[PDB]
Amino acid sequence: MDVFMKGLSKAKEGVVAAAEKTKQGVAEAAGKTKEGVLYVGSKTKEGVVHGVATVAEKTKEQVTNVGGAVVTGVTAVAQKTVEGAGSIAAATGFVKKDQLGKNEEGAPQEGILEDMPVDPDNEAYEMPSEEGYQDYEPEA
Amino acid sequence: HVNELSRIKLRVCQPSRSEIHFKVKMTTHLKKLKESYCQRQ
Image 1: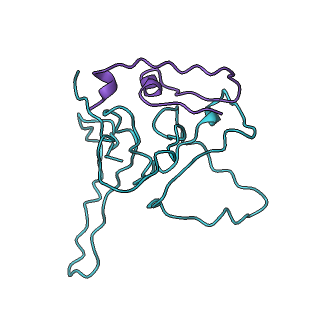
Image 2 (image 1 turned 90 degrees about the horizontal axis):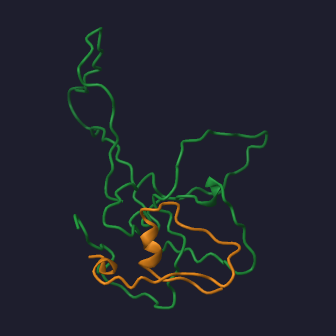
Image 3 (image 1 turned 45 degrees about the vertical axis):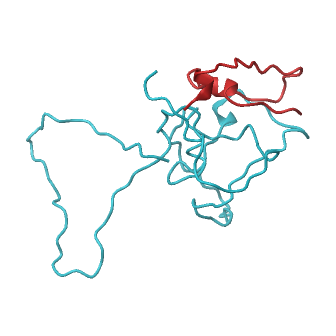
């Protein structure tokens, strides 16, 4: 049994309610995600006050009692906080499922003498024997 | 460690009424359904 462990066995400390334990809402990598498209309308709309991903108390009971909607389509699931450090992107069941995160790069800091950047690297009919591209799957 | 891999409770979750509900869209990770507990409406 290669690489087997449960990170949710004992991580940190705190006081939680034994009764306040949901069994749904885990928006992990369990769906055929796509980019999509940006659709705007004739009405601006506020779009709701945008917040941050560093949400402290991230709960989700979901009142699955007074009605509901069953969907067979892909829209039956919607992952959230997977474009950065999300507290829900570590609720993974199996130890192997690092498909919940995004790693970007870092820009130099202001207050430096000499404008030293990165080479623009302009290939001009060289054709390297190294094609393709790769993403970066980081922890949470 | 995943205790359900060393113990295997083999708990099956079957409601008396299946209407408005969902499921894990991953056969590989479908074991998480038998790695946790269910809810009663």
